[PDB]
Amino acid sequence: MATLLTTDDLRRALVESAGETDGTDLSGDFLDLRFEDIGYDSLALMETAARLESRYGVSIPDDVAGRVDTPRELLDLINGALAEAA
Ligand SMILES: *[PH](O)(O)OCC(C)(C)[C@H](O)C(=O)NCCC(=O)NCCSCCC(=O)CCc1ccccc1
């Protein structure tokens, strides 16, 4: 069953990939903002991705990783892939 995750869980899991006194306050919004904009490259970002992949049992496609500028689009990607996994 496709268990679509919420934006709350995503927010929290994005924090786990950094530490404590090295991150910003993910509050208000983080969906219409960029990853470069929040001090995330790719490496630390894939850690966040794998955090979710392993939990829901998914796998992120390679070409499609270059289609997410915003967390907004990343959420659609995972939500959509879940829907096709049934
Ligand atoms: P950054 O430093 O540009 O990239 C992080 C990775 C982990 C890819 C780093 O370059 C590295 O050491 N890679 C070794 C091979 C590896 O782990 N590959 C992972 C699968 S292939 C990566 C495809 C991507 O381009 C993913 C990058 C990404 C993901 C999500 C949003 C934006 C960019």
Image (cartoon, rainbow, N blue to C red):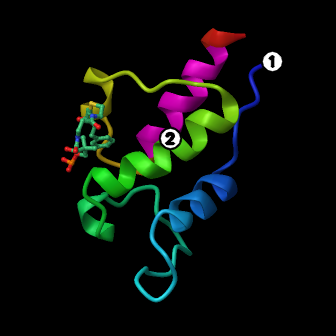
Q: Left of 8 or right of it: where is 27? A: left
Q: Crowdedness of circle 2 by 10 Å Cα count: few (<14), some, many (20+)?
A: some
Residue 22 percent across, percent down from the top left? 40, 84
Q: Residue at x 50, y 41 (%)?
A: 50
Q: Foreground residue, 59 or 79? A: 59
**From the image, which quarter does the C terminus lie in?**
top right
Which stretch did the figure color magenta? 72-83
Residue 78 percent across, percent down from the top left? 54, 31
Q: Is residue 76 magenta?
A: yes
Q: In the current view of this chain or complex, which residue is farthest to the right? A: 1
Q: Secondary structure at mark 1?
A: loop
**Where does label 1 land, which residue?**
1
**From the image, which quarter does the N terminus lie in?**
top right
Q: Residue at x 60, y 53 (%)?
A: 10
Q: Foreground residue, 9 or 58? A: 58
Q: In the current view of this chain or complex, which residue is farthest to the bottom? A: 21
Please give the label number shown on residue 25.
none
Q: Secondary structure at mark 2?
A: helix
Please give the label number shown on residue 50.
2
Q: Quadrant of residue 55?
A: top right
Q: Residue at x 71, y 33 (%)?
A: 4
